[PDB]
Image: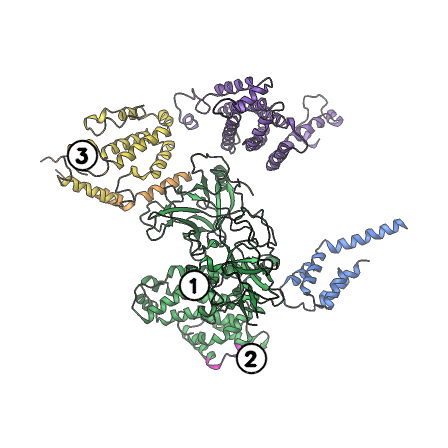
Amino acid sequence: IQFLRTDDEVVLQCTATIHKEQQKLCLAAEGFGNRLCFLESTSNSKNVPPDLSICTFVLEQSLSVRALQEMLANHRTLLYGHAILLRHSYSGMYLCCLSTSRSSTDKLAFDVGLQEDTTGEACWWTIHPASKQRSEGEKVRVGDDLILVSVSSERYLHLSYGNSSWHVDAAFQQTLWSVAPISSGSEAAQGYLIGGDVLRLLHGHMDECLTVPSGEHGEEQRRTVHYEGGAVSVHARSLWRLETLRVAWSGSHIRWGQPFRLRHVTTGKYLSLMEDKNLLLMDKEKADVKSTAFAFRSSKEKLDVGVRKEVDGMGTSEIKYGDSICYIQHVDTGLWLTYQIQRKAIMHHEGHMDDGLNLSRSQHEESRTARVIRSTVFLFNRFIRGLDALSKKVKLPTIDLPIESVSLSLQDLIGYFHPPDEHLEHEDKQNRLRALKNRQNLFQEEGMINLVLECIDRLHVYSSAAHFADVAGREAGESWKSILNSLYELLAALIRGNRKNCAQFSGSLDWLISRLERLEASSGILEVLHCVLVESPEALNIIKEGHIKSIISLLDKHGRNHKVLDVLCSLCVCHGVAVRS
Amino acid sequence: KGEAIRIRSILRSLIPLGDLVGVISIAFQMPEPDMSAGF
Amino acid sequence: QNKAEGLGMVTEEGSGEKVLQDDEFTCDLFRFLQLLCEGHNSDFQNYLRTQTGNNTTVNIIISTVDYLLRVQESISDFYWYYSGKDIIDEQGQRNFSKAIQVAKQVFNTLTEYIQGPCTGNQQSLAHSRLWDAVVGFLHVFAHMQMKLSQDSSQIELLKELMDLQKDMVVMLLSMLEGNVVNGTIGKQMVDMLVESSNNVEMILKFFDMFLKLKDLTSSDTFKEYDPDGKGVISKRDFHKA
Amino acid sequence: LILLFSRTALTEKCKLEEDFLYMAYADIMAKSCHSFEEKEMEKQKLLYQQARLHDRGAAEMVLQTISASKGETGPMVAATLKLG
Amino acid sequence: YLLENSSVGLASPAMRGSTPLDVAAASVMDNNELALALREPDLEKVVRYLAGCGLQSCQMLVSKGYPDIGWNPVEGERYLDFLRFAVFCNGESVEENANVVVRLLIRRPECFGPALRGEGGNGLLAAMEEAIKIAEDPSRDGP
């Protein structure tokens, strides 16, 4: 009897009968570095946990056809024939119809993606009562199939049959789409545990969050959970995301004893319990419910589970978010948390006298930054592995080198790290500077800078653009210098602004000067050097005669330029301290 | 009329220009009568 | 039809029923229903609500509310079409007059359905779609009266608009005929008002303007301001007055 | 001047820094402030002075300074408490 | 009524000027009033007939000996001529009819030629080249 309202979380779902096999696919979109939208199989949730974070959408506002036309010329229920505005939850971007057509077979069919312009008719979508029994002008259907039509392109949200994987494509064929009210928004209460949320697991006094090893060791070493106290709390690797087992109304308040899935947003692996070992993280491919399902309990002792299996809507707000004491217990073996800085998180039934857990909200900006970090490290790792395999061997011509994808990701990340405008309000500028500093700190803690240097070295292995083009196709060689410049600007943005990142990069300053004469990355290296020596006196302290003569030689070879003179001025005087040598 | 713009875009995507050029280039057979069959 | 009259067809809008085929037939049908339920005939009202004894029943009340919704949507679309030009032509006046008469007859039929202590009819209309049609009517009436006050050649259309508004509020009173202090119908009506908060505000302000003008005219200084009467006030002179 | 102090307080900084200008002008502004008819008249005068120095954001400036103090006892905190 | 049984009288060169579809077209030909008075219901009905004849061949032609292509071109051409008369009048295009015709055609691409449809993707130029080949080959232009 519920009705969809303005500013609520909805999921677009479609049913497929592929090879006489029924499957449910939800419309998802990466957002960061991938405008194109795809389908994620929300079925088989037991074997593989669905990722609703990139699939949930929020309806910003609904206008009628005439009202939208007038607006273009110049919590509320939804009505048939009105134009809605779908916004991606994690990305914050807006769904639309991209002019490009990925599939050649689908003639007069445009791809569906995300745009930020938010002023074109293609961004808005009109809902229609697919069911013949219902008629236009009635209230919005709930949990059932309707029709979405592009306002400008006048094409339905058709589901193109993919032999390998079904894909969405705005075409002239009907496709039945089911909505899912994840969260109504208005009924949500602050200070209470809400499903589909990222938070930290702290102790009452020991305050040692359930952290995992950082990128210092391999992922096989990071697969172990433990307890570390201190500055590790603010790091992005101390964040756990709760995923409700049920797909519909996954944004409801978490109840005591309700099973859920713990995911590590930094690495993307779900946590699970094997009886023969401790808690370990594995990818979603082998994350079964019987091993990845955990529940919160108010008391250490175990009582019968007589609670309601499924509560429609938000439901009763049992678990509070404000450091409500809880104990995690696995549904299969029924063990309890045990502790005994570096504290091993033993999983044993008797537990301990003090096993209370505090829930820290963290920040939405921190959450999106962590997801961006995970996506970027995944993309950079696959790119680096493919590039290294191509460089050292010619065994497999098929190499995973997404040049366009990595270029788009670099542009998005540079825009993300772009410094705020100085002409804004004082308070707004201060807030943006604080946010940028926090993002740089999180990236440094997660060690993105070393990976950036690694891929820059891999690109610099190739002698020239034409050489790398004949190695890896003409398009990659054409985009080689663009990717190099984007990487150098990204590194400059990461290290610029704060002193700690410059201090850490002081150790790597030698490689900049060694490769200073490449004549193609010279401007980027010079900018990075200037922005590190202006900030870190320690970085300047290790500059030597060989490096200074190298800079002067660069000036001589590349001709007269004031940037080199500015670098020399920074070397001579910094922070009001004269370096006599 | 923006709707007219949409219609023109739909027709442009429907029919390629080069195909129109090819069909406009397909010439006839100069006849000794010839029967009306053909382009 | 507008494109046709612009292009210059021979018919010259001789048959303008393409916009409302049978307004007379619609009015006759709803007047027949109203006369069926005129004299507060409780038995006939209940029979129309539910046909007891028959194997299958239909709800003429719900069908009437649906038709009211359809005509309200049509009037709203016509208002949106004429919202920009800010000028009402004679054909627009005729179409508006026919729509006003049809809607007035439908409203009178609904009032006759819900008159007296007809609890079943009152609950049916409360649970029906009428609460959206009334809000749409308030919106369109506010905007139409705002546009109509400025012009002076459409006073008859303005009066028809006010008459239909009066019939709507009489319908609301007939709904509140048997309202208790803790009335669910009262809660629904106040929810209606808060949903249509803005529209009723410009309606009330529009009435206040003239209600205060009435007392403004009869002031001693205002009366001596025009010695000869018949509006000796110039525009600027009356403005400063 | 009040906006200058407010921006200085809102500027991100690990530890509040001594500012002789802040001390002096906070003291001046604090000292600027301060039979039924005469009691009411002096009450109105006090309200006038408080409003004169207050409608320009003195309350917000005091709150920002106390917030930036970060629970550190200091002469700046003493001056802003006297101003409050 | 004429459009309901306009299927009869088609696929006949002698019936080029004598068909219920022909009289239906003549009843609206060069008449702006009637072109504006045209109706979406029967316009869509004609479009449905076009889709049917573009999805099925002619039983009479295959019985006589004409080759099977999967679609009947003569009835399709006749319906296209009807729609052309409906949309174009007095050297001008009627927007009201043109919009609905375009909507119906884009909703149902089966009305189009198999080459034009994206299922085959043969292309218009290749369609005319294959038509030329049909003309050259007597078997392709079967009895």
In-image side of A286 versus A244 (left or right): left
Residue ID at (73%, 22%) = C227
Q: Provide the letter of the chain coloured yellow.
A: E
**Separation of marks 3 and 2 at Cα, in angstroms:** 99 Å
- Give SS at disc 2: loop
Residue that label 2 marks:
A579
* Residue E125 visible in the picture: yes
Residue ID at (58%, 64%) = A202
Q: Magenta residues, as a range?
A: A540-546
Residue that label 3 marks:
E62
Residue that label 1 marks:
A378
**Separation of marks 1 and 2 at Cα, in angstroms:** 43 Å
Chain D's colour is blue
Q: Is residue A36 above or below residue A464?
A: above
Label 1 or label 2, whichever comes before in sequence order:
1
Picture quarter containing residue A379?
bottom left
Q: Provide the letter of the chain coloured green.
A: A
Chain C's colour is purple
- Give SS at disc 3: helix
In-image side of A535 versus D13 (left or right): left
Q: Provide the letter of the chain coloured orange.
A: B
Chain letter of the residue beneath label 1 in the structure image: A
